[PDB]
Image (tube, rainbow, N blue to C red; front, side, top):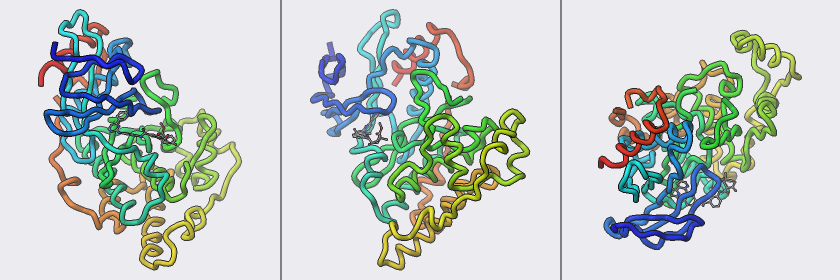
Length: 353
Ligand SMILES: *[C@H]1[C@H](C(=O)Nc2cccc(C(=O)Nc3ccc(Nc4nccc(-c5cccnc5)n4)c(C)c3)c2)C(=O)CC[C@]1(C)C(=O)OC
């Protein structure tokens, strides 16, 4: 009726007539989405087709949370929901959901390819830190931040696609993707997490921008773990006492590394060179890299203190940082229910807007 279906993008896509010229922009990140032009609002918009959201229990939990969270999150550095629609008119035959949001030119991974400058790099990192603070403002910790979860436009405006792994494993189900490269020590040691875990992830991304490759490439679960202490250093005794016994020895049992200093791990040579100012802000980069790339969680730099760091404080505007916190309605965002009950609630979620 008011919907038309397109067969390109390797699947039948049924959209409102407002969106036309559907062009596939899908990739390795969770889900396959395409690009289209929304005539009514005169803006190009990316649309995602969620296949079988209630197919299984874990599918619904990830589809349900992101749907309620992106609906009620209002931030420049977090992607937002413009319109939500489903072609089916029946809950009984309800099958698929489509998500539309502001289209962006590329992901962080692509921008990492092009080596950048201090002024642009600081702005990219600054935006990520304000997004985390807004999420931590509502009590949300992502624990899955990665260069493929982060999208940017050509004016270097940064947005975050995923809302995290929620509450919890390095062997997740089909909707999730493990992506262990940018994970913290606590995520791999099962010791527990607080809000400073995300600081670790941006540290690996910032180092990846400078170095040009993944800082800690691990073949398996703990090859990453060996990679971390190989360069940063062996954790000092106070940290090793508090881990649970079964892996506490294993941390102690493996070969000890003194570790490399950040000075030669991140040398000034690749940084911008003939400048002093870039060389000085290279000193501003390494000092903060020191404060976030510490395996000990409790004395890690926080995002609030990271946001007021001289490297990042230059862009400090309270609009992005000291924003009003988001409230989530889903009070039981801590629970699971029936597959059929899962299907009905997301159906009610999509249909009231
Ligand atoms: C990074 C890198 C890599 O392979 N990445 C890569 C390579 C080629 C093309 C792309 C790409 O398509 N990028 C891209 C284009 C357009 C958009 N636009 C956009 N806007 C809003 C929302 C979305 C969206 C929403 C949900 C799902 N997908 C997209 N898109 C975007 C976001 C991106 C990307 C490598 O060489 C190594 C592998 C990396 C890490 C990678 O990307 O792995 C998949």
